[PDB]
Image (tube, rainbow, N blue to C red):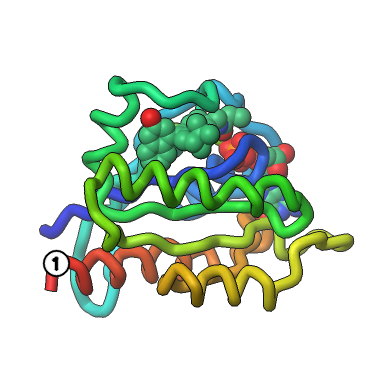
């Protein structure tokens, strides 16, 4: 079967681990150690294709390193996650997109913008502002809740479809 290597990136606390564990293990984690960086795998069917999702949930220190560049470079697509109630996490996205372009040495890398925690009140990032950003990047934007499951499959499956488009 076809393997898709996905990498989940974004600020501490946006829900990278919760999104990954909801997709792979079908449950919402109320807490997940922010030092646990690992890959999680699941066989799924997307548009009739049986495939293996190989998802790297990034964690540890906010730092640049050749060591990290080496394994991040293996990613075929990037899920760029911010939390809709954390303006700083939205502002951070630019730094992730720029480093993805650097490590992949390309202006054309499969990417999806994800606004997580859609279930929470008191949002600080307007959906239309995130939609405008995604339009400016030429990538899809999906609002998700790792808690309720809203948009979770759509976010990961859309990234798989972006990877297929790049492979042509
Ligand atoms: C609370 C812990 C947690 O969940 N964290 C996510 C993070 C670990 C990794 N992550 C991170 N932050 C940034 C950058 C990268 C990054 C670094 C590389 O060397 C290579 C690549 C390649 C693609 C995407 C991202 C990277 C990173 F993994 C780069 C800039 C954005 C910040 C940055 C300012 C260092 C944070 C802690
Ligand atoms: N209400 C709500 N809480 C969430 C959601 N996603 C993550 N969380 C919570 O936010 C915190 C940070 O999530 P985590 O997955 O550890 O974020 P990470 O640091 O990006 O891996 C945890 O307490 C999660 O339970 C969500 O969609 N909705
Ligand atoms: Mg985590």
Report the residue marked by disc 1.
167
Q: Residue furthest right?
A: 122
Q: Quadrant of ligand 3?
A: top right
73 lies left or right of 61? left
Image quadrant holding the C terminus, namely bottom left
**148 or 142, nearer to the observer:** 142
Q: What's the residue at 24%, 54% (across, down)? A: 106
Characterize the local packing of mark 1: few (<14), some (14-19) or many (20 or more) Cα atoms within 10 angstroms: few
Q: Residue at x 64, y 45 (%)?
A: 14
Find out if the beta carbon at label 1 lies less than 8 Å from the nearest ligand 1 atom: no
- In the rendered image, residue 160, in percent from the top left (x then y), is placed at 30, 65
Left or right: where does residue 76 sit relative to residue 123?
Answer: left
Residue 159, how many percent across, how many down?
Answer: 36, 64
Q: Residue at x 59, y 26 (%)?
A: 34
Location of the N terminus (image quadrant): bottom left
Question: Dividing the picture into quarters, in which one does residue 69 lie?
Answer: top left
């Amino acid at each position: 079967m076809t393997e898709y290597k996905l990498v989940v990136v974004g600020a501490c606390g946006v829900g990278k681990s919760a999104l990954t564990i909801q997709l792979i293990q079908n449950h919402f984690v109320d807490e997940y150690d922010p030092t646990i960086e690992d890959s999680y795998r699941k066989q799924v069917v997307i548009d009739g294709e049986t495939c293996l999702l190989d998802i790297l949930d990034t964690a540890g220190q906010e730092e640049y390193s050749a060591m990290r560049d080496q394994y991040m470079r293996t990613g075929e697509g990037f899920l760029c996650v911010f939390a809709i109630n954390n303006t700083k996490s939205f502002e951070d996205i630019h730094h992730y997109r720029e480093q993805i372009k650097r490590v992949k040495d390309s202006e054309d890398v499969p990417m999806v913008l994800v606004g997580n925690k859609a279930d929470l009140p008191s949002r600080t990032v307007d959906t239309k502002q995130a939609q405008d950003l995604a339009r400016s990047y030429g990538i899809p934007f999906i609002e998700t809740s790792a808690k309720t499951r809203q948009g979770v499959d759509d976010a990961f499956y859309t990234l798989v479809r972006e990877i297929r488009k790049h492979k042509e």
